[PDB]
């Protein structure tokens, strides 16, 4: 037997408590029994594992947190409720947890701790996708990771100013992404694998990509006054990463298979299984992102394959020597029959890159 | 190996060029490559047909002639861009060139411009109509003829008018018919 209370906790928190306590019994039936009165609760069961207790006990901590407005408490609460949502198969409490996640975000927000909120959302998106087979919902972790990187940019912005309207722009844009994906999570739990989810997953991403362009350009507009080559390297390497993650995300929505490599000066992106409409989308999208970022791009098309490589901040000699090797890469893939052979060919170009670059 | 050295290309022009070259690549795209630097563009292709090479050359020039505010540049664009549509085998690419032409036609100004504008539209309607086969085809043929007299009339108006204001009501009616 285990017995519990939270000393005169506010009645609103009991809404969580009662649901999660009822949430323990679902599989076992007549052998499981529990009790409560007046905010004190009990379970009469010997067979349950420690972790089954830790659903309730962490929810008890999450309730204790919920009765105070604080970004650290929010991050912990979303984390613990995420551990509950990871650990248990009942979707109803996850649906309610998403409502609480929205409520917490709409009642308070400051950017620094949104990183963990977005990470928690990313795992939730990952788990929900893994529990439903939707590839977009799994891939959305890339956009959540862009958003988490953007919180690294918002934290990095403290190098530039003691707080400013740049951080205000950043948190608002991130906040939109949060509310939008949180509503996409709510929608996915009410209408799983539906066309309405798929179109929401077509809709949301652009603002994140654009915000990341904007905030990186603002950090670049500070970095050009600092003149520090390691920070100008941070601009190059974050820029190309953000390109890479975004184009990986957008492409993978189409159901094509995509392969990604990166080497601080260059990126190799390889795609197999394409159809004309996907090509006309992908190649145009790549330009639409690349032009906004101010990055060099090179592409080839042939058959079922598209091969792609990039260069930020390039010298006129640097892009030329890159153009040699990436034209070699542009030949290498051509005859691939399957993605395991694309693996083997791309390993041979990575080993060729270990010979020269 | 064919290649197209390019300067000062715009977003719509990249969109067009990349669309039409992929439009060629699904017919005979044995291997093709394209590049962007300073946000501007470069291309290479393994020896396609001279008329397709010219189609690309034309599409480049025509697309940029559509960014200019000059009515003569707009006229050259409105005709040469219809010649891009004349070269297409894909109905979506016809729609795409059509909406570009529709935005470009919404810029039209005065009789000398208008004649070539509606003339270009009238060719395009003809090139749509003559192969359509589905139930709107018979209507569309006569619709192209219906546009044709308006061109002949806009031309006779252009030849005759001494620059008095009354032409404005007529060109507005023709603009509405055109769009």
Image (spheres, grey):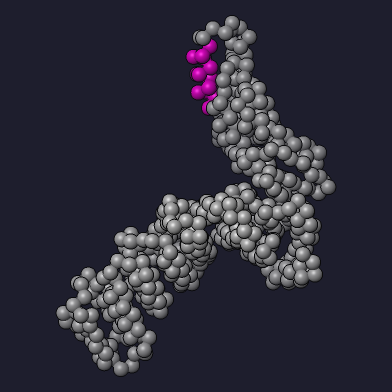
Whether A167 is drawn above or below A118: the answer is above
Q: Position of residue B140 (x, y in %)?
A: 58, 29
Which quadrant would residue A74 be assigned to in this image? bottom left
Residue at point 20%, 72% (across, down): A10
The residue most toward the bottom is A46
Whether A61 is drawn above or below B160: the answer is below
Q: Horizontally, is A323 left or right of B67 in the view?
A: right
Whether B152 is drawn above or below A340: the answer is above
Which quadrant would residue A259 be assigned to in this image? bottom right
Task: Please indicate, yes or no, whether residue A262 appears anywhere in the rendered image.
Answer: yes
| Front residue (pair A116, B9) | A116
Q: Horizontally, is A111 left or right of B56 in the view?
A: left
Q: Position of residue A151 (x, y in %)?
A: 47, 62
Residue at point 26%, 90% (across, down): A2
Q: Horizontally, is B40 left or right of B167 in the view?
A: right
Residue at point 59%, 10% (across, down): B157
Residue at point 69%, 56% (across, down): A311
Please provide the residue range marked out in magenta.
B167-179
Majority secondary structure of the magenta segment? Answer: helix
On the rendered image, what quadrant is the C terminus of chain A found in? bottom right
Which quadrant would residue B21 be assigned to in this image? top right
């Amino acid at each position: 037997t285990v017995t519990f209370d939270i000393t005169n906790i506010s009645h609103k928190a009991i809404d969580i408590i009662l649901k999660v306590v009822l949430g323990i019994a679902e599989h076992e039936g007549t052998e499981v029994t529990f009790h409560s009165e007046r905010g004190q609760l009990q379970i009469e069961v010997k067979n349950l594992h420690e972790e089954d207790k830790r659903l309730i006990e962490q929810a008890i901590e999450a309730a204790r947190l919920a009765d105070s407005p604080d970004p650290e408490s929010v991050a912990r609460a979303v984390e613990l409720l995420t551990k509950v949502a990871k650990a248990s198969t009942n979707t109803e409490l996850i649906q309610f947890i998403v409502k609480e996640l929205l409520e917490l975000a709409r009642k308070l927000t400051d950017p620094k701790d949104l990183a963990k909120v977005l990470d928690s959302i990313s795992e939730l998106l990952t788990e929900l996708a893994l529990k439903t087979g939707d590839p977009t919902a799994a891939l959305a972790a890339m956009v959540a990771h862009i958003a988490e990187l953007v919180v690294r940019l918002a934290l990095m912005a403290e190098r530039t100013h003691p707080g400013s309207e740049i951080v205000k722009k950043a948190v608002k844009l991130v906040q939109e992404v949060a509310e939008e994906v949180l509503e996409a999570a709510q929608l996915m739990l009410e209408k799983p694998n539906s066309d309405e989810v798929a179109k929401k997953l077509e809709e949301v991403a652009k603002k994140a990509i654009e915000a990341c362009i904007e905030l990186q350009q603002i950090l670049e507009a500070w970095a050009k006054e600092r003149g520090d080559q390691d920070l100008l390297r941070e601009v190059r390497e974050h820029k190309l990463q953000i390109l890479t993650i975004a184009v990986a995300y957008k492409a993978a929505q189409m159901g094509v298979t995509v392969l990604k490599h990166t080497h601080g000066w260059v990126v190799f992106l390889v795609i197999l299984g394409l159809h004309k409409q996907q090509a006309e989308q992908l190649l145009r999208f790549v330009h639409r992102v690349a032009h906004a970022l101010g990055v060099t791009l090179s592409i080839t098309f042939s058959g079922d394959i598209v091969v792609i490589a990039v260069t930020v901040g390039a010298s006129e000699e640097e892009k030329k020597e890159v153009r040699k090797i990436v034209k070699e890469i542009a030949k290498q893939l051509r005859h691939a029959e399957t993605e395991e052979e694309a693996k083997e060919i791309v390993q041979r170009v990575i080993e060729e890159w270990q010979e020269e670059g």
